[PDB]
Length: 201
Length: 212
Image 1: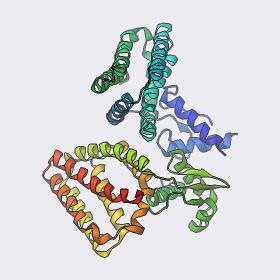
Image 2: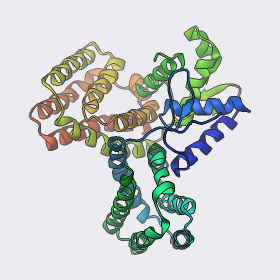
Image 3: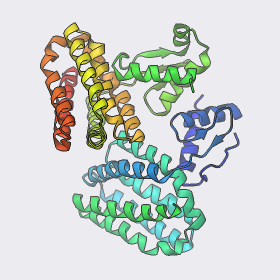
Image 4: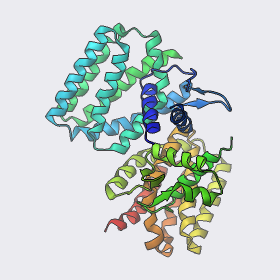
């Protein structure tokens, strides 16, 4: 029915927040679940070797580079289009999320850090009124998603204190309706976050 | 490996991409399985794969519909693919071999023949094959797949071409393709971007006539 599509959405989400380790084996009603996993294989959100079990993809440096290069263009496009549509209520909700992010970093909750970051940025991009652009960005997040698992393994959230500052600057740039400033702030955010991710190589 | 499901999926992507399926059309899984001489299973899965990327919509009673592509949606898809295709073409320049260029020249001849013969489907298809052959040399498979994905999404918007556009009025449109190939041969990055942008602008202008 429409259950299998929902199972797929749930797995895409787990992949996106780095909840699944690269190379890990996923153990599969079971029928629509298996159907969702095979559909995810077909878009390379998951891997399978012939006649064997589903696995979380391995994302090498070259592939992460390619993904970052593409989303760089798309996410900066989204933020530039969102600037002109953000309402006072939008900005207030973004400030709230930024406070949630600070809490997560202070609590040392890496799960919440990743999740709040996701919602903060997606909340911005959605306000661009470009739903297809946002679809494309989420697809890329799913592909680089297994690359985020490293955060849980090696990264101490205490060393992420200064990283929240670029978020305040982005929100300030959004509040000031400064389009080019938003692009610079978002590029800075992506750059610093990717630098953390590259340590796994 | 060859999968029946993948084969149906790629054929449906191709049909969508070249404008062979009309916006809003109701696709019946059973009809398609009968037409392909296949079990329902790989046909239904292929259709659901397209639903999962929003290339098709779910319809009542084991069926699907081809999405409606309004000007607003075509606008968004064009804006997105504009950046991606220009990025693809610029990266492909430093990797194109004499052999690559030779095959691009052959595709261009096919395109001219298609326009002279008045074969609208072949015109559309060869344009696709030509640009994709270029993009593949960017060595960015995910970028190329995403570009193909966006062509699938705008695809139903091309159905208008078969009914309303006289292929004879597209004669002069092939010159931009010659110019693009020359720019690729001369390794001129900005010239490639400019020619490809011109190609897209003129082709899009034709598509917008359907919303009048």
